[PDB]
Length: 336
Length: 101
Length: 99
Image 1 (cartoon, rainbow over the protein chains, first blue to last red):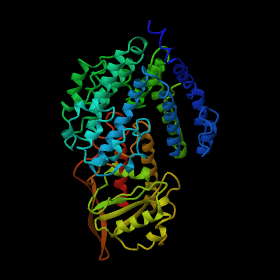
Image 2: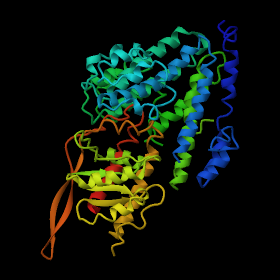
Image 3: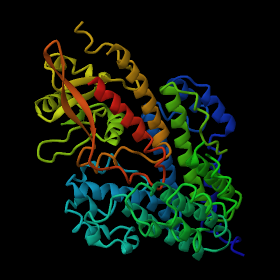
Image 4: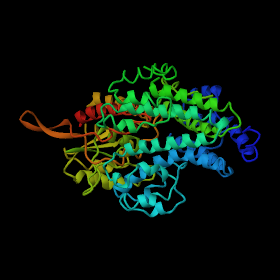
């Protein structure tokens, strides 16, 4: 029933992002880039794929790759009407949150807005809402400027006077990401059908990475067990019970046995490839599974999280080549 | 009585993470990142800025970056602070300050 | 000096290899770590050696006071970081001996 529509508005853009899926480097494409020995040979094999002639004009491989996935993402947002344009805006909030914490730091230390253009992610950018460009005021008259930005509703757990050095710089990112993941789950629950069973399993595991990676690095830190409780997103499979036992953990094995209650997250704690290299391969296992379903909006968010894996993998091939340490060159993520 | 570092972009983010950086808003920062579009004069004054500071004990600098400011560090012939030449990811340590013998 | 100035060339190749093991996983450590530093964690103490009656300046390792990148990453990464710290706390441990 919600499938004989959705091609009225998103018929062309759906076939577009399926066509951009074919430009992802496959397994056979990955093998020939391991056989390279210099960055100039790295330039030659990438001209055989869909990326070609992008280095006509080792850290330039970082920027020229990720600038291609920005303009491909910006071209998709220019044609989505109303059922999808807000959905693509939700993917940019993860990059706007990492941008704004970068901006309140220079605001606190009186480092002006001249550093904003070259040192921010172009996906979540500030080239509209020109009030933020002018603001040099120390983080209290700037929060009144900050609410003219779609991150306003996520600041309802951010008291303005709590911003002035009582909260750590890293803590305010996670409680903003906590406010971000609850809204994007509830927005994807308002949409129903095929975009509610192919997308919400991805958001459950993404909230459960933010369950495990928080508590596994919150051991030597002087943040109490009530702080890491409210930095957990109340979203995934671990919500009523697994979030409770993660607060009392204090030990590496005490976060393992609470992951042993779920057969999905155990057999991923056998990294003993490390843990985040095991969480990444399960994440691209879920984003590949979203490409199965057809008449749904989750094919766009699965494309961006795989396109960031494409820019990640080629650099890791290039860093093993330029530094000439290609005994760990096989430790990439073969997504396709 | 702290350590200074010039280095590079990828060098200074490792040594700040090591725990050697200090932000003196009164005088100056104790580090200087050099990008592709930093002039040699900016490396030249900051070498003299670190040399004239009393609290600077070591001046870490990549030899790939110290090759253009070689003429200034060859004029520094004092014992303290010690200038050190570290390898980059291109062109590691070959021929700096063992040339006195 | 000769046997250790080539030895740091391997350590600064090993630790900077961990920089590829580093933000490849967790975003980009090029603006976060260069914007919330106030005080130093590892400092120098100027001790005095002596040979043949000549006073000799020698630098002593001195880590003290706090952590500053204790909360960095922490949601993505943080295990590729803080072994990058150990790869660069050992590197700065060797480099103060050579200084």
